[PDB]
Amino acid sequence: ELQEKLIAVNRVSKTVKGGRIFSFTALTVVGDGNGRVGFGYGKAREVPAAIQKAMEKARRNMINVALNNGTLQHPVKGVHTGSRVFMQPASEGTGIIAGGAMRAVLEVAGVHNVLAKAYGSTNPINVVRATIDGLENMNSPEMVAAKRGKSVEEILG
RNA sequence: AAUUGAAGAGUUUGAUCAUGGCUCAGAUUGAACGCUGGCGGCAGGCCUAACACAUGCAAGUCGAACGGUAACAGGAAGAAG
Image (tube, rainbow, N blue to C red; front, side, top):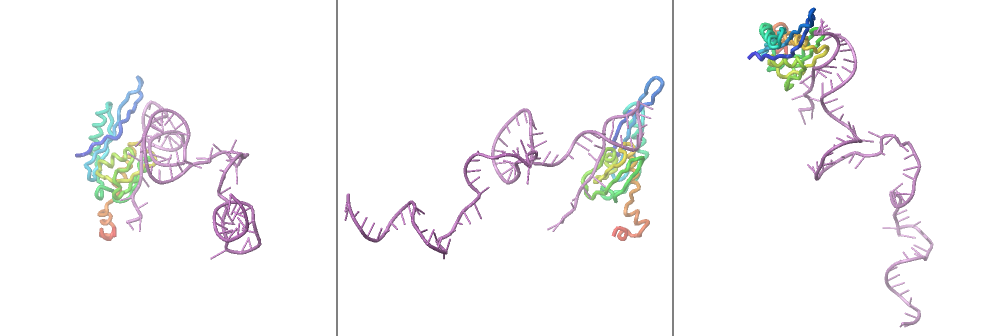
């Protein structure tokens, strides 16, 4: 129903006097499949507790995304910490043409035809914040006609 | 009707985010090499020595331009078998 999807599991260290003590970080994205999407980071000492802590963070950080018939509205960009992400509406692009950690966030939002490309750093944590900054900044023709033109037949044409 | 088209990964660190190279997954070739090998179709086939070349062939034709008769096949005569 909410399409839980783990992206990456890492292994981080802390370096104490005894030695190095390890823990695990997860990155999971959830979403219904009609324009709601959220990621949660999560970290714990073992692997399945780190993924489960990511699931609880991802459910309470969902946003709203406007999509036209399972695809985007317009070409939009997204920037977060050296991760520049470009995305196209791809009018029947027929497939989520996106890279690692950019494909997974677009599968759970419900969007199906994107030509996407990630420039800069492709660190998996930062590119998920780059796409989510790109998707909620994207506006529908109903929102643009609500503030400009005052007619959806006059805004689009 | 005459284009509908854009994926990333590994590796600097105890771990991190950056920067930044290296490397890989793709397609292609007048290809070569190794192993293997049934048929057909359509193509392609000295990229190096514009190095050197045995032998054959690759530009002849026209008698309705002309003098002609070296052959060839007949004819016309002359003989004689």
